[PDB]
Image: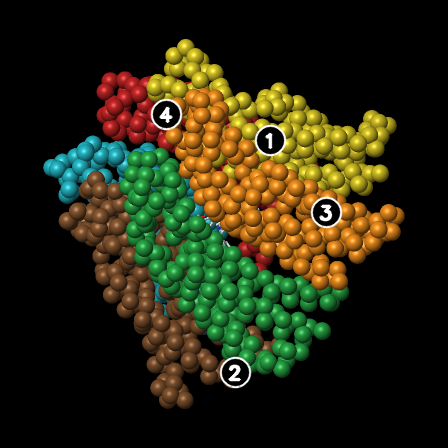
Chain colours: A green, B brown, C cyan, D red, E yellow, F orange
């Protein structure tokens, strides 16, 4: 049952790309304009927002998508050159795809966790002592985070199934 | 009378996609900037808006559209793979489409109801006791909600008609 | 003269679609941001604007365009299905197009009238008693309304001419 | 010399379309947000702006372009219909194009004049007595107005030359 | 060595078009929003900005690009018409291109100079006596101005080289 | 193996172009609106922002991408011209590409360094003495800077490998 694996993998990849490309930018549009802190100190908003969200989720997901798609591009361009052998490059492509997917999933978990809290406690200069700041659309962002994690997990499972189907003896050679 | 069913189903799907893609983003553009609460507490607006609208209607509808279209994509890519059998995958595709459509309709009803009230009563921290907040374009959003519900219901009816036409004996086998 | 009527009908349909798609969104961009009421009560602007304009003109016109174009799409997809009889579906398509056009014209008249006044008197909660609100670009909106009404009337006349040419005896059967 | 007349006419039409489509929207983006009146009365800005600029230049020019292009569309669709005679429709097309171009040029002159003043005197309700308002980018708008007038005049001259070349005897018949 | 001249000319033209189309609009987006004058007089900002920048650089460059490309369009359409002689139109096309390029370069120099100062002294009504106004991103605009001047100069040199290659005897005839 | 070297070079070039075109504009959208200085002097924000960021990173990267792609365009157009010899232009194209890449990398290092500080100290007129200003999203910009530097370094290494493979004897001739 390897053909169904590839079918589902392609469908899931397209689904993830479409969802991101259509809604991600709109969800994270006013992340900084609607981020407000309870203070009068100029520049506290910028520092506290920067500490709270070092990298926006959408940038990370775009980078992940492009990086995960890279090996297929490598294989396609190698095939194009080879005309005007290919049974070995495929195994290395699969291995690299597996590694990249697993790494990106683990990185997302270690970077963002599983939820976006509605309050933040900030103690960065120039803010005096400790201040409280309020986030925009925490619930929608939490839902988006969980959904992306689930899709990435499905992709990882399918890739592992494909790699196992190929077998360890072929991978070693 | 199965051909007219498929014709109407395709027309309705295209109609829904076009309507959403053309007007949905514009309708819900200033949902948060025009949402105002009667208070002086910083951060009350963000919390009350997040509680009032955990997920925007437009994103739910986009997700529904992509998810409902997925099975056709799976069938098409399976057909492409088969060339360079198909009379059985079709039944499962129809069943899954029916299930997804019914589930999404029920979920919409249980999430949003049938109207968008013009006032909201919010008692979430940091707001003090109860505060009153005012929504933007409640009537247009109500009309959009009802129209989308009606279109989804028509799609459900057509899908059920198709499934019944196929017959229970074929579905069992 | 049915064929020359068809030529004119196609030209006017394309003209209407182009005009809407190019200028409608820009005209109605700042309808709510520039709508101001003479009061200090929070939330009066939102309620009064919602009462004044339950549905924006542009969205109504987009819906009308798609709905009017639907029957041609149904006929085209039926023709595609028939290959890989057609002289009867055409009459029903014409009748439905006529009915839809007339209904949309009447609905526009009953919903918006023939002008957009520059002042509005609003007595909706939370506004205290009666307040006065001021509209944005009333004259441009009036011109747009009249122009769309005229184009729709021309389309109705051409459709009626075509239906009359087909004759009542054919329509009956 | 009819070859060069048609060549220049086509080039000029394309030039005008490109210039409008590329710069018109950007020039007139902040016409109303940067329009300011010297008063404290709410609603005076809206009324005075509406009186000063009943119709924006860009929308008038877009309407003119589409209307002027319409006869060519009619001729092309008639030619398409005729396949799956044409030596007469061409003369009427030319006459209608000439009439439309001349009418639009005269209308522009009578609507906007030749310059956009930097100050406006407004005495419209609710403004008290007479107030002074200030326009945004008057000089760029004046340049755009003059350039469009010159291009339209060139088009009119070329169309008149073409019509004269056809001759009065043919036009009469 | 004429082929290299044409190759470099085409490459430079494409380079200029790409650079403008990609960055010009973004650079000059907030030219008027961030232009601030030290005064309390309403309407002083509009008048002083209009006096400082009668025409934005980006619009001048767009006009220059289209005008310079026009003669090639004229030649191409003449060639297209000629099928369903050409060795003479080419010389006039080259001469007109040279003249247009030189004229636009000189006009840019006489209009904008070589730098955008960071301060402006304005004495236009309604501003009282002299006021000081501050520009947005003077350095980026200076860099853009110098770069465009250099590219236009390279184009002028290449066009002059081509024209000289053709020779004076051929041009005279 | 330059074959796989060229494969990797093409893949990394496409990767860089995609990343820039998709995220660069969004990251640097509100660079100036969110830049705030601790002062009351009008015009201090503009001057201090201009001194802090003479040229935005995104524009520099766009210019670098187009300039680096230019030699391939020159070679392609020369090949097109040659039809309706080519073994020497390739070496010069490679040399020029190497030089451009190295120059742009060095320029980026000397212009921006390796980090974007969160505070800036500004002493430019009209600001009185020395003032403190606060940057927007310093961490995301630092990450972007480092990532672009790494990608450019990889491209430089691959280009150097290709040039070395071609050999010094061929380059000399
Ligand atoms: C005018 C369009 C702009 C809007 N987004 C930012 C740059 C462009 C395009 C891009 C988006 O439409 C988009 C298109 C295609 N693929 C995408 C893939 C990912 C993505 O992530 C935000 C956005 C994508
Ligand atoms: C510059 C264009 C941007 C505007 N919207 C957000 C990202 C892109 C595209 C998309 C919209 O045009 C759009 C296009 C196509 N299909 C769509 C399907 C659904 C949709 O839901 C809002 C929007 C769609
Ligand atoms: C980035 C582009 C966005 C701008 N408008 C909203 C969603 C998209 C597209 C659409 C408009 O360009 C448009 C395109 C094509 N047909 C249209 C038909 C009707 C229409 O009514 C406003 C707008 C149309
Ligand atoms: C996202 C794109 C939007 C920007 N303008 C408003 C609606 C759309 C398209 C249109 C413009 O690009 C445009 C394209 C093509 N032809 C045009 C013709 C005239 C025009 O006048 C403003 C604008 C045109
Ligand atoms: C949604 C897109 C809009 C953005 N700019 C204004 C109108 C349209 C297109 C245009 C720009 O993308 C553009 C495209 C193609 N050629 C251009 C050539 C010149 C240019 O100068 C600003 C802008 C160009
Ligand atoms: C409506 C679209 C506008 C958005 N950006 C500014 C002008 C246009 C296009 C461009 C961007 O989509 C884009 C497209 C394609 N290639 C690009 C390459 C580089 C780039 O750097 C910001 C932006 C690119």
Q: Label 4: state its secondary structure.
A: loop
Point 45% across, 54% down: residue: A58
Query: Which callout, 4 or 2, points to the residue nearer the camera?
Result: 4
Q: Chain of mark 3?
A: F
Q: Judge by depth and name the residue closer to the eye, B166 or D11.
A: B166
Quarter of the image with the C terminus of chain E in it: top right
Find residue A41 and report its horizontal and vertical position in percent. 33, 35
Q: Label 3: state its secondary structure.
A: helix
Residue E151 in view, yes or no: yes
Instruction: Write down the residue under mark 2.
Output: A1
In the rendered image, the residue lying farthest to the front is: A129
Point 31% across, 41% down: residue: A129
Residue E35 in view, yes or no: no
Q: Chain of mark 2?
A: A
Can marks 4 and 2 be said to lie on one chain?
no
Instruction: Report whether the residue tagged 1 is closer than 8 Å to ligand 6.
Output: no
């Amino acid at each position: 049952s390897t053909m169904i694996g590839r079918i589902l993998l392609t469908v899931v990849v397209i689904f993830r790309i479409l969802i991101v490309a259509i809604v991600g930018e709109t969800v994270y549009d006013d992340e900084q304009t609607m981020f407000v802190c309870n203070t009068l100190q100029p520049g506290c908003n910028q520092a506290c927002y920067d500490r709270a969200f070092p990298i926006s989720h959408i940038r990370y997901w775009v980078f992940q998508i492009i990086m995960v798609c890279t090996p297929s591009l490598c294989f396609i361009t190698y095939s194009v050159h080879q005309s005007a052998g290919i049974s070995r490059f495929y195994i290395i492509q699969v291995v690299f795809r597996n590694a990249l997917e697993i790494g990106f999933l683990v990185g997302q978990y270690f970077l963002y966790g599983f939820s976006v809290p509605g309050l933040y406690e900030c103690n960065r200069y120039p803010c005096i002592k400790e201040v409280e700041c309020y986030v925009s659309r925490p619930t929608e962002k939490t839902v988006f985070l969980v959904f992306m994690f689930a899709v990435s997990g499905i992709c990882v499972v399918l890739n592992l199934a494909e790699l196992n189907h190929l077998g360890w003896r072929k991978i070693k050679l």
